[PDB]
Amino acid sequence: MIPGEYHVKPGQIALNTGRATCRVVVENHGDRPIQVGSHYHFAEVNPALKFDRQQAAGYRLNIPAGTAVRFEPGQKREVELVAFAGHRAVFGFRGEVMGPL
Amino acid sequence: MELTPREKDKLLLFTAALVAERRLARGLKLNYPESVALISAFIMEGARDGKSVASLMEEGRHVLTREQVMEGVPEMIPDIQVEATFPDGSKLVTVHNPII
Amino acid sequence: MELTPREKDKLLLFTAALVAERRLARGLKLNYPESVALISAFIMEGARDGKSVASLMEEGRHVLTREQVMEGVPEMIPDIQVEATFPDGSKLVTVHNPII
Amino acid sequence: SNISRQAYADMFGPTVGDKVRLADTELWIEVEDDLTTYGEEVKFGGGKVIRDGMGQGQMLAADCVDLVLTNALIVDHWGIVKADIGVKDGRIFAIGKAGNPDIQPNVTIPIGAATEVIAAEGKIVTAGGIDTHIHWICPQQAEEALVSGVTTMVGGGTGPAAGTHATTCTPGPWYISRMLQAADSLPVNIGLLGKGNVSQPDALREQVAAGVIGLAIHEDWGATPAAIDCALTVADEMDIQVALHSDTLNESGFVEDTLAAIGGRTIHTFHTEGAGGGHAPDIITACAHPNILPSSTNPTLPYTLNTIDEHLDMLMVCHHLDPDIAEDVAFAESRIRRETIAAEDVLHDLGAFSLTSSDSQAMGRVGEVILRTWQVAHRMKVQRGALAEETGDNDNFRVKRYIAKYTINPALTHGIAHEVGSIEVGKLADLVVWSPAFFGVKPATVIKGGMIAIAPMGDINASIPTPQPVHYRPMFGALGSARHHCRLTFLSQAAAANGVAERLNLRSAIAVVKGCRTVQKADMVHNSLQPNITVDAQTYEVRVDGELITSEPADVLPMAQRYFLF
Amino acid sequence: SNISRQAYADMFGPTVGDKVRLADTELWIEVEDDLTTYGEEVKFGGGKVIRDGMGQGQMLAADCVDLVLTNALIVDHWGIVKADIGVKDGRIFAIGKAGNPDIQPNVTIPIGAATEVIAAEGKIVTAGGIDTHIHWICPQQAEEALVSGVTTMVGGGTGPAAGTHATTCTPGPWYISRMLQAADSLPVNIGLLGKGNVSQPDALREQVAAGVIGLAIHEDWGATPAAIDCALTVADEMDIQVALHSDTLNESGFVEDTLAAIGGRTIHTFHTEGAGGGHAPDIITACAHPNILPSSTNPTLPYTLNTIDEHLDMLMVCHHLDPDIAEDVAFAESRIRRETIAAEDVLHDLGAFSLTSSDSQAMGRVGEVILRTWQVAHRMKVQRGALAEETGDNDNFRVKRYIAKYTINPALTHGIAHEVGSIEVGKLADLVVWSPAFFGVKPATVIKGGMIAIAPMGDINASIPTPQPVHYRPMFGALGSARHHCRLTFLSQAAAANGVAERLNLRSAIAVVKGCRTVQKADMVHNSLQPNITVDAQTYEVRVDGELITSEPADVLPMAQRYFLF
Amino acid sequence: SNISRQAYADMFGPTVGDKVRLADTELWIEVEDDLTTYGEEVKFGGGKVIRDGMGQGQMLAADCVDLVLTNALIVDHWGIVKADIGVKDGRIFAIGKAGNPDIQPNVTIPIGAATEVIAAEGKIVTAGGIDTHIHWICPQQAEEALVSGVTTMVGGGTGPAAGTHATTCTPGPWYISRMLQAADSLPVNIGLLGKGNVSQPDALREQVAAGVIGLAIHEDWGATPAAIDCALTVADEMDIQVALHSDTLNESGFVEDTLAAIGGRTIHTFHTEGAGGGHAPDIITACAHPNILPSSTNPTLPYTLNTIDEHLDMLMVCHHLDPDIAEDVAFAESRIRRETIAAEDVLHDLGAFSLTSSDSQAMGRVGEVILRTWQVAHRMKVQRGALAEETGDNDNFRVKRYIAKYTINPALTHGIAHEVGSIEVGKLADLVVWSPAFFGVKPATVIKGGMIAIAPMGDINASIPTPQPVHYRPMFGALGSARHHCRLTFLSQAAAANGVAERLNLRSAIAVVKGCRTVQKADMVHNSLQPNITVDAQTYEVRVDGELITSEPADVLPMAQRYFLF
């Protein structure tokens, strides 16, 4: 007996189903580490990360909400992106779009 | 003495610990509040003695064992934190999974 | 610990009892507040041990005798009541004429 | 991508199909529905979702909520579901999916710059409790109750005076006015009850006009047929509630005479089992009537090994009886029957008894209303098993039935359900956050009118709010003017019209009661059973449809020695 | 029918002829009169008298009292009688026989639906104490005094500052205004004293116009003939009182020079014995004059074995003296004389000294004014026996003489006797309920303006209000707006006229002082003796009519170690 | 006549040339000047100087001060001098020679009947501290800070909610209004900060118009270039301050990108060293810029043996990170660098870092801002010796440099220096009295707006205020209306114009902020160094002009175990 214990039924949850995704190779050309969040507009990340910014337009990391992907200096890795939903209007970040798309 | 609010608050923790201490002595299996108070007071005295934060983070896990507390208690306490005046000022001591 | 107001209030009773306990040990004849605190604390520990309300209503009358308290004290205490968490929840213990 | 259910539960709390144990009891709830879109859950923290342009939008204050409780597991009479809770203007805005409509799908609760966040993942959220049997013996009771999870207190009193010790009555205009003023200083919603024991209507009308939301009839002031009829007549014309504590002595008649005097009019019966007061030994039979709204006081909930032993001395002190007067002790003894005490627990499980209350410091414990309600549910599951209404392998229905007893039902009975009582849109944001291991025992957060009023708090000088010692301390919602803005003082329609609030210069928000006369047993949520119950005059045995109703006394109970220092 | 006297006393309290011991002292009071009609006493509880149609009537709120104290044993300067006390609109309505005129005879205090009940059978009821020597060093003093049974506090100060440590002065308009505002937060009636040490009238008039009800002259600010004359001139024109602490150093003259400066004008002398301050070593001779209203501070009451030893260090800290400065220690020593200390107790017993006060945290104990007054009475009965005025075998007269010292006399001296000071109709309902075993030590109930403000209270979560731990806690009468309505802030006639209350936005009820100039020694109730007293300049011996006045130091005292935990 | 210097110091405190040790540290201050006329010092007490016609005059209230602090040793950024302090109308009237112009020479501070006295001989008097990094997690923080010597608190929060746990933001109009109302109940001057993380200006303008005096940007809500630029644009047009907690993750760019976004506009950087948050690992380089006003949070001050060990778990709880999530623990570890921690102490000693703050209950200790600032000064003197600016054999300059860090500089940074921040005429009388042995640890008296608000107080029932137990208790300055009159609620110019105070019915005095945009590093008193600082991306080494900056961890510290019970 454990007070307030859970009895989680076994299995898995499929995240962000029914949405456009794409894979991109990314490389950190900076001398300091860079960590990117799940809902951050990938196309507007730290300029030191080199990748096809044009492909990442209107996309974010296809990872569970609240987690992140870290890039140590010189690190290169392929990540999977998922497209923004809702109104598909981007405001903030580096101020590159500030509107729909 | 010029006791500040924080010193008077710690007197509450000390007294709570006196209760648990006596019950443990009788041979009772401590409950949730008793366990937290007993381990917390231990750490405070550790700091008064001048032990390091690192030493206490370890020693704090050997105050009470799983057989000295009620069922479910060890899981209700994933960690215990308390601050005390060490020789080098106030420091925070975090003991993870104190009861095993 | 997440101490509620009632738990913190009981800590006052416990501490008051610590005072009386020490004085009784020195061989002093306890006064009114000391006697009430000493017997009350006794009952609370009884409940923690798991004794029944009925048992304590009896045992509570054999904590202090007429020769261990000041004159007039036994008559100032026609009864003593205190509540504590028994294994089956909070219960009220009423000890009539505790000092004889 | 994909994530395992266990890892998911550890991050955002349980989802559909997962079960959770309530504290250390045998009750298990199962998540019935989840309003989130998997992958789009909002989470706060360094590098999380709720950040500018991401889970937080660009909308103005008017277009977003003031407070959002993320990933909460709601436990209410209507359902046990996972969802975000939006709070705006001190009231429940919506129950749905929070976020930023600019980049997230299905957002019903918009988060913007004006939104504060409370992380409820892994926590159970409920409505604030409502105790309708308060004796205002001391102001300290409000804090004790608030800490336990009760946010609304209805009752009467003027302080530690003989009348208040025994009854829930605030006698007359002067004391009513004084208490309405004193209420502004207390962190709970309050509604007062006046002394309804009089056979002259005008004496009652004055009180209602002064501010009371009900009239409490207690045998200590004489619960006679004439008094009862008088109070009910005034109640019928002023839309206020009547709470009854009948004639134990059978001095003016038996229970059937009282029921006759009531004449099918709506009335709330206090401690219907009888130990706390009422026609000996069959007041319990009142729960069979449609116009009767029955409740229990907590010292008899649930039937345990020490219950009886404790009751005799408790009875005496409360009602100012004399142990040296034979008649006083005989009348006390006629009130404590093992038979009715045991039956009460079962009648609650069946829904025959619809409310639970304390009866604060007068044969009741102000901070144990919620705690004891759950102990009864535990003991009933253990002894009787699943309810006929249960579906699936969980105790969901039994949980909804019991939670309604100290939330929506008390609110309906006293005509304040339009303001509080449950987690529904438009109602005051009186919410309680619980960690599953401490459910019903010690809350993590108690919210009043949209502001946290009390919570466990560690070392004030610590580097974080978690270091010991951790004990309950008053928060901003309990401070001066912020308090006034986050609490409600309930008035009768007459008092409100008379300008009582302005005359007394009441600083808190005002709410008016209504619908006290129209409520009936059939309206009590999940507790509308009108059983064919009988009590044997000699043996005191309780029977429903001829079958004997009884239960066994508990030796050990959950939500007890594992959580309390004393 | 018939009932034995013992059984009667156990049920309704003592009646005519019965005697009662005051706490654990040797003082015994005897009931002089009983206003009840045997068989018609009102009692509250389950199945008792105060019930609809029985001991409770059908009258409207306007025709019955708000509160009734049943079967009380009143101990006041005018009598020691058994009776019910009626309270209406926060004031004493009547002292008589309560009940329902419909079925009971001789009812003078009608009980109705609007009536709250306080059971006082077996309890002694007195008026609230009044301390006229408060140093507002800390706000915590009000609670300490309220708990002891003192409901009105007169004095001055701004907090723990040097000036307030030594004197009872609230210096100037700004601080006076600030303290008048802060007073609304305290549960006791308050009247402020300004700094009267100035030789320019206008500087004093401003203060009176700002709100003070008196001017305190203390030697620390220079108690010179010019200052004294100045203050008395302003007092004479503004109807406020002057309180004096004379020149101990004899720097400007001797006691006769001060008396000359006073010029036969009304004045209240603080700690007239001298230990607390005054012309060394004969300030005590002031009590022989008709215009002098003499009072004592409590650390010297009564003369005990440890009194002297304790005084030297106490003196130094209070007046900011330096133990390393010869002149500072010599002046301290000239103030502590065993001779005058012993005589003071006798002069009180004789009625030469008319008031008792504390001198809070400046050579006085704020919570021991009442306690010490009774200890002196005990020690005097023990040493001197019955007073010449006693009749019967009781200490009734000595009790009336001593109770007047901290009740009616302080009220008369400061011109507030029209509002408080005794249990008389029309006066504010400031009452204290005492159990005979704890009389003068620990009250059962402290009522302010008709509402209980503080009382012993047990476990808040208990089933009754009696379980341990029991300690004093604030009640509704001490809460926010209810407090404001139940307390009084006394203003000078000038301040009231100037609209000070409205300008400062004072929330409490306002009362104005009057009759400060017309009171004289002859007006002090039971304490008007003007003895031909002399003090030997060398031996410090006190003599009245040539006979030596003295007493012996107590080794053990009542109302001490039997009641206190520390 | 003549008196020896030692005897003189014992009577009136130290004079020119005398040195005094600060608590138990190695810091020594030397009296630079004395404004008295030897022989004419004013002293209060029985038979002292401050008496009618002597050291006290005949002037009316308007011509004399309300409060005088006699023989005080002032320690402020402008000087360490001996003098009397005059206080009138709640503000600092003059710093000079108090007395009676009628008989004394050079009197600049007239004492009259309306003057209260506080004896400060042998005591050090300073201005009240100002903490600009408060997380309003609980109301109890105000008392803790007040006791420590901090009289003004700037920050944000709504109580113990996730958002407030991590950030200093009071989100939106509703919560801002609620907190402004709750502030009237707290004994410290208060100014709120809103959530500045938004890319829509109007969402920020609403908040400023609602009442906030600044906008706090925290990485938890997304510290992106767009958000930063947005907040600074609104700040520039509304004259409010921006406080930054940069992007540790380097998610949107590195420190140079953030600095670029700031675009040379005025901004206050929180915990510039980085442990509390900021671009890893070089946020510390911001202190080289003219538009940057850098401050430190206290858990890293000063570098000791246990600092590092303590930080990891502290970080996690504050920012709601998950120790089981690799990315969460890596980002926590990247924040704790021994290299930057050690350099911070030196940068403070050099004046590169201009402010010290707490970061209350979110990686900071609310009652240790002052205490830790002095510990750093001690450790720096011990390790580096005298500052290049020192003159004479004392630490006077180092003391002025460090005291400015928690007094005048915080006031200048947030545009409230016209009201508080130092002991200068016209400023609010927020003063702290310290005994030299307890300097920076436990105050003797804490004055707010001219009234003592909190002080150590002994037994309430004692004959003097000195007997044990002595602990801090609220005084009259902290009571109801007197409190409102002695505290300030700072509003933005927009809020003040909009009538926010009247609409919310705020009872306290209102003050408006101004000059937030014009302040720059060069304006920071004694702390304007803009060093050519660099941080090695790999080794984290801090270098100024190529030279390595570092210090050694303390094993034992002053103002620690000798003063605290726990």
Image: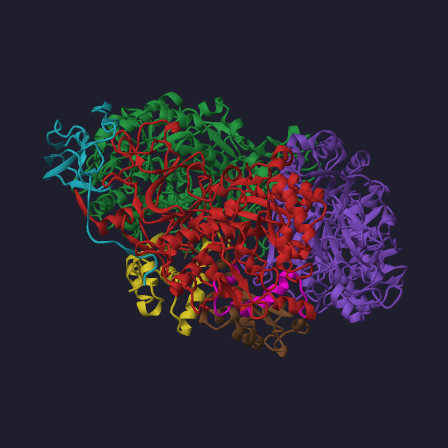
Chain colours: A cyan, B yellow, C brown, D red, E purple, F green
User: Where in the figure is residue E408, as x and y percent of width and height?
Assistant: 79, 50
Question: Do we see residue E312 in this rendering?
Answer: yes
Relative to D442, residue F474 above or below? above
- D544 vs F537, left or right, is right
User: Where in the figure is residue E174, as x and y percent of width and height?
Assistant: 63, 33
Between residue F296 and residue F438, name the one nearer to us.
F296
Q: Which residues are magenta?
A: D298-323
Question: Is-magenta flag for residue D57?
Answer: no
User: Where in the figure is residue E80, as x and y percent of width and height?
Assistant: 82, 59
Residue C69 picture quarter: bottom right
- F481 vs E84, left or right, is left
Residue C75 picture quarter: bottom right
Relative to F298, residue E18 above or below? below
Query: Quadrant where the N terminus of chain E lies?
Result: bottom right
Q: Main SS type for the magenta part?
A: helix
- F514 vs D322, left or right, is left
Question: Is-magenta flag for residue D310?
Answer: yes
Seen as rendered, the residue at the extreme front is D546
Between residue D533 and residue E436, name the one nearer to us.
D533
Relative to F17, residue E29 above or below? below
**For the image shown, how many numbered marks are present on the structure?**
0
Between residue D308 and residue D538, name the one nearer to us.
D538
- D97 vs E126, left or right, is left
Query: Quadrant where the C terminus of chain E lies?
Result: bottom right
Question: Do we see residue B89 in this rendering?
Answer: no
Between residue D530 and residue F223, name the one nearer to us.
D530
User: Where in the figure is residue C80, as x and y percent of width and height?
Assistant: 59, 68
